[PDB]
Amino acid sequence: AFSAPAAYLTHQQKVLRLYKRALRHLESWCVHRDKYRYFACLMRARFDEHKNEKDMVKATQLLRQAEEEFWYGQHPQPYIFPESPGGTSYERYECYKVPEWCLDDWHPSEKAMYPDYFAKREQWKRLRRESWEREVKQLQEETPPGGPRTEALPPARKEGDLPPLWWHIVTRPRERPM
Amino acid sequence: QQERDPWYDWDHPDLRLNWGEPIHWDLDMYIRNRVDTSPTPVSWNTMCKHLFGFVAFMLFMFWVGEIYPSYQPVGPKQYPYNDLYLERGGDPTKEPEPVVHYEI
Amino acid sequence: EHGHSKMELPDYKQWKIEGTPLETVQEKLAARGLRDPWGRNEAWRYSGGFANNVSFVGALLKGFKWGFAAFVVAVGAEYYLESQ
Amino acid sequence: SDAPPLTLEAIKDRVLYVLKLYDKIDPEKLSVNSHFMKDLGLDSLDQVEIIMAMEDEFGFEIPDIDAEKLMCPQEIVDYIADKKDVYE
Amino acid sequence: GAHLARRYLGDASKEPDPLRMPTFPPDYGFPERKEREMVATQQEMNDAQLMLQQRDYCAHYLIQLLKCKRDSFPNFLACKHEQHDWDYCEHLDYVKRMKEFERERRLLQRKKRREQREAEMARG
Amino acid sequence: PDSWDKDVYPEPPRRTPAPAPQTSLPNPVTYLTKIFDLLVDRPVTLAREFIEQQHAKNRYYYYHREFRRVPDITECEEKDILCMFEAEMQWRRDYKVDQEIVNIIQERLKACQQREGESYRQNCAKELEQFTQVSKAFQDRYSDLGAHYSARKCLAKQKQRMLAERKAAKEAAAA
Amino acid sequence: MTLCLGAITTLFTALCAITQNDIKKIVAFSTSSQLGLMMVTIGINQPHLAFLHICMHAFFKAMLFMCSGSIIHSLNDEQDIRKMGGLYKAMPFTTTALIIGSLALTGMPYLTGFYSKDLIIEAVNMSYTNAWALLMTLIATSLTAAYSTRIIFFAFLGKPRFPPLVLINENNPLLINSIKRLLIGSIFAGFIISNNIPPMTVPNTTMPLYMKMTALIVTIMGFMLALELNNTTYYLKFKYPSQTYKFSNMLGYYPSIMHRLPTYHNLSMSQKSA
Amino acid sequence: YRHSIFAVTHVLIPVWIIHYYLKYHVTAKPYTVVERKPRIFPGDTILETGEVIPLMKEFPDQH
Amino acid sequence: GGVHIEPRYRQFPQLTRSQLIQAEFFSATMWFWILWRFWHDSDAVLGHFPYPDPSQWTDEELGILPDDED
Amino acid sequence: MLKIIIPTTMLLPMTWMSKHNMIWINATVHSLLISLISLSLLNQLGENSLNFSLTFFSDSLSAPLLVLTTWLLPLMLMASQSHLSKETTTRKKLYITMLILLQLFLIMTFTATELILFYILFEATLVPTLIIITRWGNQTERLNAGLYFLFYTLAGSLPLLVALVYIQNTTGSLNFLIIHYWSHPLSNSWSNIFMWLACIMAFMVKMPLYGLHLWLPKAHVEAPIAGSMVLAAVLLKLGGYGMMRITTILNPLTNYMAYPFLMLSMWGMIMTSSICLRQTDLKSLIAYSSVSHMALVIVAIMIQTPWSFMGATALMIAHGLTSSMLFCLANTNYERVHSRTMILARGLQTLLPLMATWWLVASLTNLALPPSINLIGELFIITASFSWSNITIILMGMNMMITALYSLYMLITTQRGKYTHHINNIKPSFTRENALMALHILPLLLLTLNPKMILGPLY
Amino acid sequence: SFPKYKPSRLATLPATLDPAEYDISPETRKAQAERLAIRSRLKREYLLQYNDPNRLGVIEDPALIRWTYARSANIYPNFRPTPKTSLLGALFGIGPLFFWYYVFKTDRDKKEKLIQEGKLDQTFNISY
Ligand SMILES: CCCCCCCCCCCCCCCCCC(=O)OC[C@H](COP(=O)([O-])OCC(O)COP(=O)([O-])OC[C@@H](COC(=O)CCCCCCCCCCCCCCCCC)OC(=O)CCCCCCCCCCCCCCCCC)OC(=O)CCCCCCCCCCCCCCCCC
Ligand SMILES: CCCCCCCCCCCCCCCCC[C@@H](O)O[C@H](CO[C@H](O)CCCCCCCCCCCCCCC)COP(=O)(O)OCC[N+](C)(C)C
Ligand SMILES: CCCCCCCC/C=C\CCCCCCCC(=O)O[C@H](COC(=O)CCCCCCC/C=C/CCCCCCCC)COP(=O)(O)OCCN
Ligand SMILES: CCCCCCCCCCCC(=O)SCCNC(=O)CCNC(=O)[C@H](O)C(C)(C)COP(=O)(O)O
C-alpha cells in the first residue's frame, strides 16, 4: 500500500506469497491453535526440503504444481481480517472521511470557534505554499530523462526542504475520523 | 474491476482506476457494484451442474411426493347439519338432499 | 473519563508449553524430527481462567442444580399445602 | 468500542514481547534495532512468520509488498504507528 | 405409517383410497345403525360463531370452554375440566374415524375374499 | 345518532351479553375502562359541550339543491344541440347518482361482513344478493362505454340489448 | 405450491447454515429456515399456528441476534467464529442468554419455541401432504439443532482464539436489561400466550407415541450428530473437503451463478443492442 | 416529574384528540367504526332486552 | 453507565459478582420452569389419550361378515 | 380566462422597463402571483366544463396542466439566475422574454376551445424553445438538437393540419363541444385509416413514442436548465393532452389501429428503462426515464378506459414535477463539476447532505413509491391494462423493477461511495438551490393528499 | 493428481494458474518494464497536478473523455451495414414487437370470443 511496486515479482517473492497464502488458509482449515501449530510446522517442513534446489527449471515446475494444489485446497471461505479488502468492516468508516479543503468553505462564524486550529492550519498552508515551489524544482532536476521509470519519490536532501508531493500523504483525514 | 489489486494505491480507490489509464468499454458493467468475473474456488461448469442437479432433483421429488401423499389411517371428518349446508353457501329455499353420518 | 490505568504487560517467562496440548503437539513433532518455534506464543490461551473447560452438556446444564433444588422445595410446599 | 488508545511506547513493548516468545531468537540479545537477517541470522520464511505473528498480535494485516521489507523491530513499530495514526 | 407402505408397495386395491371413503353403505354391517347425536343447535352455535371447521360433533364442549374462558378471564387456568372434556370428545371422534377406516378396510378385504371364492367356485 | 337515516344503512339490534363473573378475582379490564372514562371521556365531553353551545349560539342552515326533470336524449332531435346538452347533463347526474347507490350497497356489504364475524358466509346472504342485483343492473347500464361515454352511446347500447332481447323473445314464443 | 416452497426453503437454508463461519450469517440463515417453516405451516392450512410461530420467533431470534451483537462488540468488531474461543466464563450473561435462546429455537419442551414449533411438527405429521415436504421439514429440524450446536460449540466451549489484548466487558445496564427482557420473554411468553388466547383450531389429541415424540427425537439426533462431528476437529489430522461441503459452504452456488449469469447478460444486452 | 410531564404531553394529549375525533366526527358518519358482534353462549342475558338464552340439551355427562 | 473494567493482555478478564449471580439466577429459573411445567403438565409432551390398535377391534364391532350374510 | 392571459402578457413590459439589477426579483414575484391566481381554475364541476367564452374553456384535464405551467416559470427563473450572471442586460431580458412567451403560448394552448387555434399555439410553442436551445446552450451539438427537435415535430404535425382542415370541411366545425356532441363512428376504410394516422402522428411524435424519440435526448441534454425543465415537464404533456381531445372522433377505429402503438410503447418502456441502466450521462438518463414514463402514458391513452385516463393525467403531472426536480439536481452538480458525467463526481452525500436528501426524495418519487401520485398514475394505468389484457402485467412489472433499479443506481453512483479526491471546488449548496428543490418537492407531497385535483375529467 | 480448474467468461483464470507467468522471457521483462514506465509517467503527471496548491478545479482526464465520446458520439460514423448488423438489428428490433403482437392479439381474440359466447362470468366487473 505504501511502498511502490516493481515491474514484476521475483521467484522468492512468489515463494513467500504462496507460503503466506498456504499458512493462512491452513489456519482457516485447522481452527484450533495446537492443531494449527502442528500442521503449520508440517507445512513448513514440506515447504523446506526443496529449499536448496539449484536449477531454476525444477524450481519453476515446483511452486507451479504447488499453486494448483493450493487452488484445490484453498478453503473457499478463508478468514479475513475485519479491515482487510474482504472483511466485514473494510470500508465501514470511509463515509466519515472528509477532505481538509472543506474547512476552507466554513462560515466565519464557524471559524470563530476553534481559532487556534485555524491559526495552525494557516501556518501549515504557508509551509505548503513555499515547499511546493521548492519540490517542483527538486523533482524536475532529479527525474531521469524520458520520464520516471518507477513510482518512487525522492526524499528531501536539503535542510529546509520537505519531501516532494507530501501534502496529500501527511494530511490524510484519519483512520477513524469519528 | 473487483479483481484488480486491492492493496495498490490507486488514484480512484473505490473504482480501482488510475488517472490516464484506459477506462475499458464496459467499465460501468464492472464497478464492484455489479457483475464481477473473479475466479471461483470451483469451476463454473461444476457449479452449474451441481445447482441444476439439486434443483431438478427437488422438483422431481416434490412431484413424486405429490404422487405418493402421506396421511393417517382415518376416515373423512363428519359435519352434522347436511355437511353444514346452510353455513357454507346457504340457499335455504331449496331443501337439499338429506345426507347423514354413521355412528360406530 | 475512560480506561487509562497504565496497564503493564505480564512477565514473558511465565508462558511454558508444560501441561498443555502444546506438549502433545511438540512430542508428535519431535517424533518426526521437528520442533515448533511459536509454541510459547500461544501458551496464554491455556494458563489463566482458560485452563478449565466446560463440556457441551455441562454448558447446557448451567443452572440445573439450583433449579432442581427450587423445584423440589416448591413441590414439597405444594404437597404440604394441598393435604389440608 | 471502549478501546484504549495505543501509544508508541505500547506498540514497542508488544512487538518485543512477541519477538521474545519466538524461541528461535535469543531473548537476551535481541534489541529494537536488531536486524532479523544478520543480527539474528534468520531466514526469509522466519521473517514472514514474524510478520504473521505481528498481524495476529495487532489484529490487522500488513500487505505483502509492505511486509517483505520490514527487517527491524523499529521498522515494524513505525509501520504500525503509521497505520494506526499514533503520534505519541 | 405402515398403511402407506402397504398401499404403495403391496396391493393398492386391498387398501382404501382416503379421498373416497366409504365405498359401502352404512347399513351393510348391521341394521341397528344408531344415529349420531348433536347437542348444539343451529342458532346458538351460529351465535357463538365458533369456526366453520370447529362446527363438528364436539361443538358443545367448545361452547362451554369458550364460556368458561370468558367468565373466568383474569385467572386463565380456571377451567381445565371443560378443555379436557373437549379434548376427550375430539379423541373419541378421531377413534370413531379410525374405526370407520378399519371397517372400510375389512369390508374391502371380505369383499375381495368373496369375489375370489366366487371365481374359484365358478372355475371349479 | 340522528345524523344519518337508519333505513338506508340498516343495523341489527346489537344484542350483547351481560357481565357474569365466575371468580372474585378483579379483572383489569373494568378498572382500565373506569380510569379511561374518568381521565379521557369526561374532558372530551366537556370540551364538546362547550363547542356545541358555541355552535348553538350561532345557528344557520344550508340546503340540498333540487334539480328539475328535463327531456332526455330519447326525445331529442338529431341536430338539436340545446336539448342534447340538457339531456347529456341530466344523464351525467343520473350516472353519478347510480354510482353513489352502488357505493351505498357496497358499504352495506362490507359492514355486514365485518359485523357477522365468523358466520358471514351465511348471515350476509341478503346483502350479497342485493349487491349482485344492483351490480348486474349497473354493469348492464354503463359498462363498455369507454372514456368518451355519452348519453347517445348508452342509448345505442340499450337499443342493441333490447333488440337482442326482442329477437330471443320472438324465438321463444314461436318455438 | 406454498407447502413445497416452504419445505425447500427451510431445508436449503438450514443446509447452508450448517457450515457457515460468520455468526450473523448463521443466524440469518436460521431466520430464513424459520420463515420456510412458517410457510410450510401456511401450506397445511394452519394460519393461526403460523402467526403464533411468528410471535415466538420474534422473541427468541431477536435475542439471539442481541447476543451475537454483544459478542461482536466485545471482540473488537470480530464476526468470524474461528477467532471466538472460550466465552462460557468470560461472558456469563451472554452465554446463558444464548443457551436459553438456542434451546428455545430448537423446541426445548415448555419454552417459547415449544408451543409453536412442536404443534407445527405435529400438524405436519398428521395431515394429507407430500411425503418429500414432510421429510424435508424433519431434516430441517435436525439441521436447526445441528447449527445451534455449531454456534455454541465453536463460540463458547474451546480455548480462547481472539487477539491477546482482552477487552471483554458485559457490565453495561442497557445491554443487560435489554437482554434480560427478551430472556423473560423467551422463557415465559409462549406459555402465557398459549393459555391466554381462545382456541381457533382443532387439536391432535390422539396420536402414535412415536409420532408425538418425533420432534424431540429429531432434535436430539441433530444435537448428538453435530456434537460428534464437531468433536473431530480436535483430532490431529487434516483432510481435504468433499463436494457436499463445497456445495453447502458456497450456498448451493446460487449466489454466484444467479448474480453473474443473468445480470451480465441483462447488462450487456442493454448496452449492446438497445 | 419528567415521566409525569412526558406522559401528559405525549400520551394524554394525543389520546384526548383521537377520542374527540373518533367519538364526535368519525362515528358521526355510518359504518366508519364497525364492531364484530360479541359472542352469544347459552345462559347469558342481554342488557338491552333482558331475556335469557336457553341452556343446552343436557348431554349425558360422564367423564 | 456501567462500571470501570480494565484490559488484561492475555489474562482472564475481570468479572463482577453481579453478572455471575444474574446469569446463574436466570439459568436456574429457566430450569425450574422446565421442571415445574413437566411436573404439572406432563401430557403436553407424552399425551393423555392412549392410541387405539385397529387389530384389537373385534370383527362384529366393524360389522364384518365372512361372506355369510351375502 | 383573460385574468391569467393579460398579466402574463403584462410581464414583458415589466421586464423591459426594470432596473438592470431587478429583473429577476420582479419576474419571480409577479410570476408567483400569476401562479397563485391560476389556482382558481382548480374549482371544476362534475358537469361539462368552465366555458369562459367562445375562444377559451377550462376542464378538469386542462386545469392541472395550466397550474403546472404557471408554477414552472418562477422555478425556471430561479434555476436560470445562476448561469446567466455574466450575461448582458439586453440578452437576459431576451431570455426572460422567451420564457414569458413560451408560458403565454402554453397557457393559451390548453384552453383553445377550437382545434385550429389549439394547433396554431401548439406549434407556436416550437419557436421560443428552439431559440432557447440553439442560443443559450453550451455544447456545439445544440444546433443538431434544435434541428432534430424542430423537424421531427413539424413532420409529425403538418398532416395533422391537413386532417383538421378536412374534418372542418366535412363536419362544419372544429369546436370541441360541437365535435364531442355531434361525434359519429369512423368506418373501417383506408381513407379513415389515414385520417386516423394523420390525427395521431402529431401527438405521438412529442410524447415521444418509442422509435420516434431520437430528438428527445438531444434536445434535453443540449438545452439550458430552464429549457430542459420546460421540455420535460410541460412540452411533453401537450401531445398527451391533444390525444385525449382528438380520440373522441377516432372511434371505433382505435379498437384496432392502436395495436402497433400499444406494442411499440409496451416494448419501448422496457427498452428505454434498460437503456437507463447503462448510461454515462445524467441528463441522458433522465431523458430516457421521461421516455419510459410517457410510453406508459401512451399505453394509458390508447386503452381508452376511465381508469386509463385518470392514471394518464396523474402520471403526466407527477412526471413533470419529478423530472423537473431531477434536471435541477443534475444541473446543480454540473455547475460545480462542469462535466455532466455520472461517474466522475462521486460520494457527494459526504459533502452536500441536504442535496443528498433532495436526491433521495426525487429518486423515491421516480421509483413510484406509494402513496405518491406517481404510484397512483402507475397503478391506475396498470389496472386498466390488466383489464385490457392480463398478459401486460409481465411488461409492467418488469418496467417497475428496472425503474427502481436504475433510479437507485443513479442515486448510489452520484451520492454514495468515496468522494473524488482531486475535485476541490464543491462549494456548499446555496439557499437558492435548496429553495428550488423544496418548491419542486412540496407540491408533490401536497398533491398526494388531494388526488382528485389531478385525476382528470373522468373522476 | 487433483482435478483441474476450467476457467469461464464469468469465472476467469487466476494469476497464479496462468502458464504465461511461468514462461519467463527477456521480452516479457522488458514489456513489463515498459508498462511500469508508462504507468509511472501517468502517475507522476497526475500527482504533479494533484498536489499543486494553485489548482482549484477538476483535473481533466482525457481517458474519461475518450471513454464517454467513444460510448456515445463515435458509434454511428464507424457503423457499416453488414450481415451481422442487419440481422441483429432486424431481430432485436422487430421480432419482440411481432411476438408481443401475436400474443396479445391471440389473448384478446379468445377473450372476445368468450364474451360473445357469454361464458366468461364477468359478474362484479364494474370498474374497467
Ligand atoms: C423412519 C426412520 C427414522 C430414522 C432415520 C435415520 C436415522 C439417522 C440416520 C443417519 C442419516 C445421516 C446422518 C449423518 C448426516 C451426514 C453428516 C456428515 O457426516 O457430513 C460429513 C461428511 C463429510 O464431511 P467433510 O466433507 O469431511 O467436512 C469437512 C470438515 O468436517 C469441516 O467441518 P465444519 O467445521 O466446517 O462443519 C461441519 C458441518 C459440515 O458438514 C457438511 O458438509 C454437512 C453436509 C451433510 C449434512 C446433510 C444431512 C442431511 C442431508 C439432506 C439432503 C436432502 C436431499 C438432497 C438432494 C441432493 C441432490 C443432489 O457438519 C455439521 O455441522 C453436522 C452435519 C449434519 C448432521 C446433523 C443432522 C443430520 C441428521 C439427520 C439426517 C436424517 C435423519 C432425519 C430425521 C427424521 C427421519 C425422517 O459429509 C458427507 O460425506 C455427506 C453425507 C450425506 C450427503 C447426502 C447428499 C449426497 C447426494 C449425492 C447424490 C445422490 C443421488 C441423487 C440423484 C440425483 C438425480 C439427478
Ligand atoms: C419506426 C418507429 C415507429 C413509426 C410509426 C409506426 C406506426 C405506423 C403503422 C401503421 C398502422 C397500420 C397501417 C395499416 C393497417 C391496416 C390493417 C392491416 O394491417 O391488416 C390487414 C391489411 O391487409 C394488408 O395489410 C394490406 C396492406 C399491405 C401494405 C401496407 C404496408 C404494411 C406495413 C408498412 C409499415 C411501414 C411503417 C413506416 C412507413 C413510413 C387486414 O386485411 P383486410 O381485412 O383485407 O383489410 C382491412 C383494412 N380495410 C378494411 C380498410 C380494407
Ligand atoms: C414523425 C414523422 C411522421 C410523419 C407523418 C406521417 C403521417 C401519415 C398519415 C398520412 C398523411 C396524409 C393523410 C391525409 C390526411 C387525412 C385526410 C383524409 O383522410 O382524406 C383521405 C385522403 O387520404 C390520402 O390521400 C392518404 C394518402 C397518403 C399520402 C402520403 C403518404 C405518406 C406515407 C404513407 C405510408 C405511411 C403512413 C404511416 C407512417 C407513420 C409515420 C412513420 C381521403 O379523403 P377523400 O378522397 O376526400 O374521401 C374518400 C372518397 N374520395
Ligand atoms: C491448505 C492450502 C494448501 C497448501 C498447499 C501448499 C503446498 C506448497 C508446498 C509445495 C513445495 C514448494 O513450496 S515448491 C519449492 C519451490 N522451489 C524453491 O523454493 C527453490 C529455492 N527456494 C528459494 O530460493 C526461496 O527463496 C527460499 C530459500 C525457500 C526462501 O528464501 P529466503 O532465504 O529469502 O527466505
Image (spheres, rainbow, N blue to C red):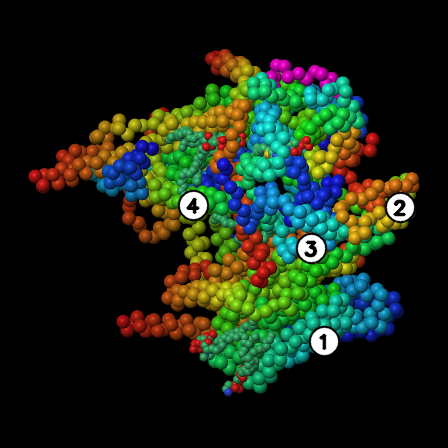
Badge 1 marks a residue whose secondary structure is helix
Nearest to viewer (mark 1 / mark 4): 4
Say if residue I50 shows up in the picture.
yes
Amino acid type of the residue that numbered disc 3 sits on in the rendered structure: Pro
Q: Position of residue J351 (x, y in %)?
A: 77, 49
Amino acid type of the residue that numbered disc 1 sits on in the rendered structure: Val
> Which circle's residue, 4 or 3, is located before the other in the chain?
3
How far apart marks 3 and 1 lie (CA) works out to 43 Å
* Magenta stretch prevailing secondary structure: loop
Asked if the beta carbon under badge 4 is closer than 8 A to the nearest atom of ligand 1, the reply is: yes
Q: Quick one: which residue is furthest to the bottom in this view?
A: J169
Q: What span is colored magenta in the figure?
A: C9-23
Q: Position of residue D42 (x, y in %)?
A: 71, 26
Nearest to viewer (mark 2 / mark 4): 2
Return the residue at label 1.
J127
Amino acid type of the residue that numbered disc 2 sits on in the rendered structure: Ser
Q: Residue at x 81, y 67 (%)?
A: J27
Task: Name the subunit of mark 2.
Answer: A
Q: Residue at x 67, y 72 (%)?
A: J149
Q: Residue at x 60, y 31 (%)?
A: A50
